[PDB]
Image (cartoon, coloured by chain):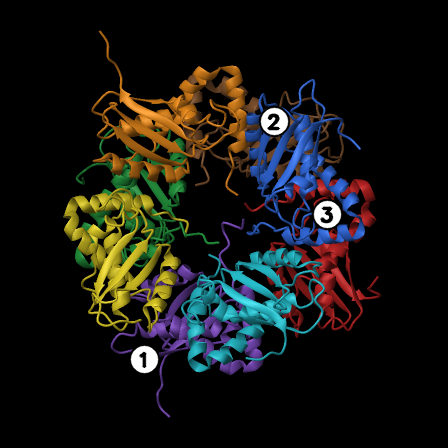
Chain colours: A brown, B orange, C yellow, D green, E cyan, F purple, G blue, H red
Amino acid sequence: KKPDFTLFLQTLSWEIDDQVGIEVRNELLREVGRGMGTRIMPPPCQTVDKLQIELNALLALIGWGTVTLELLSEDQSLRIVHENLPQVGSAGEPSGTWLAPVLEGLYGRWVTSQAGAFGDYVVTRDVDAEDLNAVPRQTIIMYMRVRSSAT
Amino acid sequence: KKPDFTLFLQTLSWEIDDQVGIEVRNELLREVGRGMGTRIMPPPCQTVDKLQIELNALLALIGWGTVTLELLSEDQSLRIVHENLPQVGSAGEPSGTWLAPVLEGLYGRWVTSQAGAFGDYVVTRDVDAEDLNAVPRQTIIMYMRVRSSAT
Amino acid sequence: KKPDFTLFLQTLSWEIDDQVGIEVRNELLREVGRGMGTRIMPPPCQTVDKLQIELNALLALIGWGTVTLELLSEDQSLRIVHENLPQVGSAGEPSGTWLAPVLEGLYGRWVTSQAGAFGDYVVTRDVDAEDLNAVPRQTIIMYMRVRSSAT
Amino acid sequence: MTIFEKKPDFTLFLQTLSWEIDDQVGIEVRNELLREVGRGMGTRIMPPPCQTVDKLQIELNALLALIGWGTVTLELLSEDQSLRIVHENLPQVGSAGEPSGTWLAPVLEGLYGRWVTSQAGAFGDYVVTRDVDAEDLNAVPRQTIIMYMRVRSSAT
Amino acid sequence: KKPDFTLFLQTLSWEIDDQVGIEVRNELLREVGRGMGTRIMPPPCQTVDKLQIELNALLALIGWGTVTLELLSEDQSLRIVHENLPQVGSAGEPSGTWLAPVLEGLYGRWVTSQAGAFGDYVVTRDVDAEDLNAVPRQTIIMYMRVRSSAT
Amino acid sequence: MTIFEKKPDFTLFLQTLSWEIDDQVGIEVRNELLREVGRGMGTRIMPPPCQTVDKLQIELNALLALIGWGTVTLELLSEDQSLRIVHENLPQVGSAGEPSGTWLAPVLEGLYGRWVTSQAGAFGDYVVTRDVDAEDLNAVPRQTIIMYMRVRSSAT
Amino acid sequence: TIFEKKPDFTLFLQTLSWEIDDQVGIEVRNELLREVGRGMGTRIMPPPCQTVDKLQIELNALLALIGWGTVTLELLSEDQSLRIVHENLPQVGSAGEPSGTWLAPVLEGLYGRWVTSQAGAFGDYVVTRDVDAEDLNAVPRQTIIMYMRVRSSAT
Amino acid sequence: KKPDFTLFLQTLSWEIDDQVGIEVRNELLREVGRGMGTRIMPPPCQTVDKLQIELNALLALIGWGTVTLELLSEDQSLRIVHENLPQVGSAGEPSGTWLAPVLEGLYGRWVTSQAGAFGDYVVTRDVDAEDLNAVPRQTIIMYMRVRSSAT
């Protein structure tokens, strides 16, 4: 009686892909991720550890999984490991991860609101470590250039 | 703990309506409706009463509301009254009913499926009956009629 | 509690009806009710009022609705009004009441087990009554010949 | 303030139904009826046209999740000319069935029979049948059902 | 999934009822009420209206219904109306209200020192008021009074 | 307006009940009460007549699942002429009982005693007794109850 | 190995609300609660809406996420105001004026933030709780009446 | 419809921290803990093992995790290991443990109450026994020892 949207998103994912292709679809969904991050937001956090907690609490709110943030000192990169991306049928690459670019946008926006970053513009989905590690299907690894920010 | 898609659909609906406009959004949503209708289907119903029960059972599966069907034998039609369309933010005409053309596509398939397949039926929404009858916001009134007549 | 059987029962009701017809089906269903009645049962109750309470606790355990019992001052009968019979699609007479004969066997077993009945053989459901009151679709009204009155 | 339990439980009803049918008609006929019911279920809830086995697997599992009937894995065996179907957590309806607890298993043969046909570029007349020796050499859990989809030799 | 004790309590009430009096069972239950009152308690509330809110919060914690408190200055009493006492089969007077004396003890512990009422009080079930008001089976009426009185 | 979802919790009532009863009468009068309550529960919910130990185990798990009282395994030990009953996840009702947390354990004695007898056929006369010392070689969890079904002696 | 039941904060809020009221007055507590409200508003927010009806729908969806009730908005032309009726404020014991409405100032703060974001180039609004019209006639204990009026927000 | 307070508490944790700083917030929170313990309480417990069971029952009632109590010297010392303290954003030392002082105060009242009243005990959080043993973030290690208690 509380609405379920799985089936709707399953059919919507198929129709969109069919109509506009992978490239446009990915852009639409990043843009949706960015929009989502302007309706729900972390406070201004001091540490990456504190940000991890603020974000996991936002994810729990909508049941979209969990995330670990690792601050790599080279490229001053941020590794984002997202667990339990919701599944909406077989669409996406790999199959099941159709909603993965939404995360690119959402994290783009959420982290950029921390001021250690350069904007919500580019968050890179790693394909290599998402297929060389034998990472679970709904686990999404991403990378982000950051500034020299700490802890 | 089950994923909540309300926020994603709120933001997706704003995004789509900015890029493509009402009429293209409506045509995509109906097609999604048609696709849902090839995924979940009622059995061959002998009467409208029996069909109405079968349709409510399918609506129960995904929590998308309740339906009453009424044969308007004078008016060559069926009145479809869908209570409780799931609400996905303020988009749609009227506001709150973005998902309505999905119903049009879904009923189109569901009602033209078993015994309905004989006869060239269409299902279209009444956007004057909704403002005319003071129906609740998430109530969608639709009619099933035959296609064409001319000279 | 996790597996759902509604869809199974829906298609089971259609398959059984088509192979054996209404009459054999009613007999299979009554016999199932009597079997259910030998697996869960009330204690021996002195009064109809107390049996009413015991029967509703049993029904609450499986979610099959509520019942009121009425010892008819003297038809030498017991009126059973059962509310919210589980709906199993559109099969049954009237549509939606496929599971109604199970109740006949269930109350035949449950009541007989108390001081005052002649066996689980005959519980007749009232058809004309269900159309005298204008009774909701899932309210099932039944009558049992009874020995003498338990208050 | 009461939840008028809109969780009707059908487990007790199904336990007694299963005992009752097995008493009246026996194993072979119970199994055909159940396969037929499975076919029926497969005309009400359906996957979309999938290009690959792995995509089909995801689509089937979303359908089972929708009704809480377990999880499935599909594996192509070219050497055996078959698709292996391993269904886990078949709902248990009491002790009927062979082995006990697996009364509902034939419903899967009919269901997977409806759901796997014309999927992933498989074109023809196929039968999903259950394999009781396969379940055994595995030491498979009680509610795990193993089936093979093969080209039809005889059964329909 | 979580244990249900309704069946255990239905059988328990019967077994305790058969071995000992109505009255010995009622004193046992009253003592269990006092017991429950040493395990969950309200804060010291300034008014009777604040006590009512606090008592309902404690009732909601365990799901034992709701309470209204009325000061009756003339009659020198606090009327206590408890709605939706859990039903535990058909034991008790009237049937269904077997747990009623548990409230006598419980409200006994919960009310005495609140609202600037400083003395020695007894909470007593006024059964004769439950039929005076055409009160549902699971509604229990109690009066909080000063200790000693006549016929 | 109040909550759409609250069904009554009896845990708190039962912790305080177990306490008062222990206080008024001793352990053994408490245990005999709860045995009798168990026998009474065995008359309200029951298994069909089962062919085998495995089928009976499944049927009893179905009954226990109906009320949320745990799971059970049954083993025929044809050398002690006994049936070992291992009940897991006995509902805990405070700290009463021996060991603490197992107050409800004699309900299981009565309950299983009634179920087993219903399944005795023409030739069986059984009693079920709780074995607390064999809860030491198992070093079982607190809410696990071990019982033995044995032929009744009926001698002196 | 997951924990099953989600934590309940009802009891904790009941004790916290007593202790704060005991330590500081109605007044310090209320400005404390209004600032939490404003802080909540920077974390959950509506998109920019073009009408009041559209804003009403967007707010009810925010409120639905955290289960904090429902709101209706009504623009009043003859007054310079928008009436905000909030139903089912979560009840957190008997603290507050009236008892049970302790969380109400969070709402002033919350709607203050949301409504400022909705205000265009010309608006400069304050939202204030109107107590003596909640109790002018017969609104439920957990129904809060607020008015949004034109004048600068802070103090 | 079950109001969620996580977001209120995240924001309140920041506002309180901002205004008064760590030591004053902590003392407030210990007072809250003691107040929670005058509202929900264990019974008399002859042993630590009986207390542990009763304490876990009270915690399950509110969903605040689990506890193991270990006696080190018969009357001298108790170690209290608390699992799954509710997380409430990134506040607290270490981040995520803002609610920890409440436990100091709750256990202070729980273990101090009944037997344990006769010791003049104080419960205090060990901050580098948590990290020396590399305990989970929401696991709180406290000790009960002798020293002055009241204000």
Side of F4 relative to D131 (left or right): right
Give the secondary structure at mark 1: loop
Chain letter of the residue beneath label 1 in the structure image: F
Give neighbour class at mark 2: few <14, some 14-19, many 20+ (Cα, 10 Å). Answer: some
Is circle 1 on the same chain as circle 3?
no
Residue F25 screen position, x and y as percent = 54, 82
Location of mark 2 (residue): G75
Report whether H23 appears left or right of H114.
right
Residue at the location (51% across, 69% down)? E100
Q: Which residue is mark 3?
A: H98
**Is residue B112 placed above or below H21 in the rendered structure?**
above
| Residue H23 image offset from top left, x and y in percent | 83, 49
Q: The residue under label 2 is which amino acid type?
A: Leu
| Disc 1 target residue | F125
Mark 2 or mark 1, which is nearer to you?
2
* Residue type for callout 3: Trp
Look at label 1 and name its amino acid: Asp
